Amino acid sequence: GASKLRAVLEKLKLSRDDISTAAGMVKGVVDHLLLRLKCDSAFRGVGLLKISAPNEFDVMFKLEVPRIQLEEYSNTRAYYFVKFPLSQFLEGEILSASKMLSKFRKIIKEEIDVIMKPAVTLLISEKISVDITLALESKSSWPASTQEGLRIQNWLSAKVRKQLRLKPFYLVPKHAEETWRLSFSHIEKEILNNHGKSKTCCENKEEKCCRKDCLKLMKYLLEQLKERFKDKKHLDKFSSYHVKTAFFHVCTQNPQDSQWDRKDLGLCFDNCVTYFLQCLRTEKLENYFIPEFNLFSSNLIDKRSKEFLTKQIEYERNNEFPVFDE
Ligand SMILES: Nc1nc2c(ncn2[C@@H]2O[C@H](COP(=O)(O)O[C@@H]3[C@H](O)[C@@H](COP(=O)(O)OP(=O)(O)OP(=O)(O)O)O[C@H]3n3cnc4c(=O)[nH]c(N)nc43)[C@@H](O)[C@H]2O)c(=O)[nH]1
Ligand SMILES: [Zn+2]
Image (cartoon, rainbow, N blue to C red; front, side, top):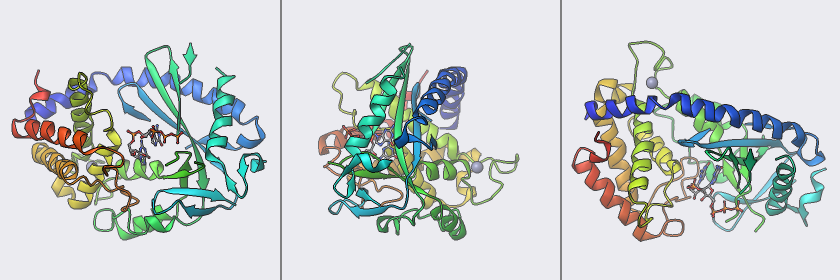
């Protein structure tokens, strides 16, 4: 379906000045929050670690904490308690996510045409929504639950996995409670931008793969379907993170750049859609870094919404995506 999909990618490029100038003011607001945040004892040394869905922007504020100790919350491989001026957020020996997240919020309140709402949400001039997520930074080795994650050996190399896992990891105050959740959104950006088996993937005309186009098509497929099913709101829980995560699994499944040749955009997209479909139908989408953390368990998304999106994605697939027409 190259023609139809290439037309879609060409349509998306048309809003490139909208995504830029809208994030162009996200910038000057985030720098302003960063300035006065660095004036508070607890948030000194905070710094910047972007577009989720047209006009939905995400910024992560990283904060360097001293040596950190993690206790896995129950058997949820992603959620943890945290222990070691930061002393003010303590609940005994653990560091209170809910309480730290709370002072963050209030410092941004007195700093704010912007208005409020793990994410603190701003609204710049009504159109532009910004997610501002506080991230604790740990330079310790990654937690045990990531040992079998990041299965990039056959795709990027074994040595690249070793380089990636020497980098810090992050905890956002997202409670399953004073609990924090692992974050590797910095690693997600690295493997997205440095995505080939060939180190020179997409640096010359002989190596133009279609990995990034497939993810765009997949993000756009979900955005369009979510728009169409706005009457009965069955798709509210699915995000482009479910799409990005599935796209990482397909990259692991098709590790060679030859499996992402631009000429094959139609078949590559089909691989992304079929694997996403298998995830919905088996109620299993593994976090790329934490395999025993199922983003699609009936815990997070009930079975009816998943069965719903299957049928729609299945119909779209079997009919050469009429959602992409005209
Ligand atoms: N976006 C995102 N999701 C991630 C990441 N790593 C794991 N996940 C998990 O993927 C699922 C997709 O969620 P979403 O993006 O559609 O929405 C998530 C989350 O569900 C929502 C908060 O909803 P809540 O449960 O009602 O509240 P919460 O428990 O967060 O409240 P509190 O903070 O008081 O505890 O927020 C979205 N979200 C999650 N993490 C982030 C993040 O880092 N940035 C932004 N902008 N939004 C986020 C979910 O199951 C999710 O956990 C990951 O890196 N990104
Ligand atoms: Zn490439």
